[PDB]
Image (cartoon, helix red, strand yellow):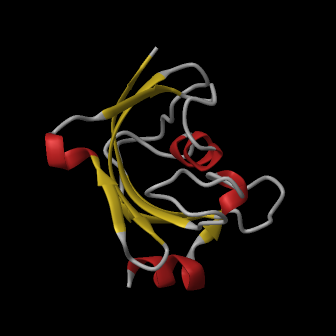
Amino acid sequence: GAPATVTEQGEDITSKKDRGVLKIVKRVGNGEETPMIGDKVYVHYKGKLSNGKKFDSSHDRNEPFVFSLGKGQVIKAWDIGVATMKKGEICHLLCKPEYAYGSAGSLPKIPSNATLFFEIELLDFKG
């Protein structure tokens, strides 16, 4: 499935090159610009545990997820991953626990030491 395909074929976009955040571009975005640190970014996402269990989607309530890029308002994997995206891009990200919810997890949805999969669409970004 999607998660396994990222495991086998995803690009390692961590600076440490520890396979903590693995990426596949699924739809190419617009031009060359990526968001700046501090930008307001608007995304749609579909989130699963690595075993395929859906835990959330912004589409269920048609409500884009909004955050300030690089501010730690989201899991490290999103600060890293979304910074690499162009407007209109869809990617798949696979996120080791060290770049997500670590040993604590986020119960009830996210167990301790969970690797998470996301399909993310970068809808827009603003200053």
Q: Relative to 64, does residue 7 appear above or below in the rendering? A: below
**Which residue is rendered at x = 58% and y = 67% of the image?**
115
Whether residue 121 is visible to the viewer of this picture, yes or no, is yes
The residue sitting at 60% across, 66% down in the picture is: 114
Tell me where residue 11 sits by quadrant: bottom right
Q: Position of residue 63 (x, y in %)?
A: 21, 35
Q: Quadrant of residue 86?
A: top left
Query: In the figure, 21 relative to 45: above or below?
Result: below
Give left or right: position of 104 versus 125. Answer: right
**Residue at position x 51%, y 43% from top?**
82
- Horizontal arrangement in the rendering, residue 21 relative to residue 119 (left or right): right
Q: Is residue 13 visible?
A: no
- The answer to whether 117 is drawn above or below residue 79 in the figure is below
**Residue 55 place in picture, x, y as percent:** 36, 59
Q: Residue 112: horizontal and vertical position, in percent?
A: 64, 63
**Which residue extends farthest top?**
127
Position of residue 72 relative to residue 107, above or below, is: above
> From the image, which quarter does the N terminus lie in?
bottom left
Residue 80 pos. (x, y %): 63, 45
Left or right: 98 in relation to 111: right
Q: Going by the image, does 111 lie left or right of 52?
A: right
Q: Nearer the viewer, residue 113 or 64?
A: 113
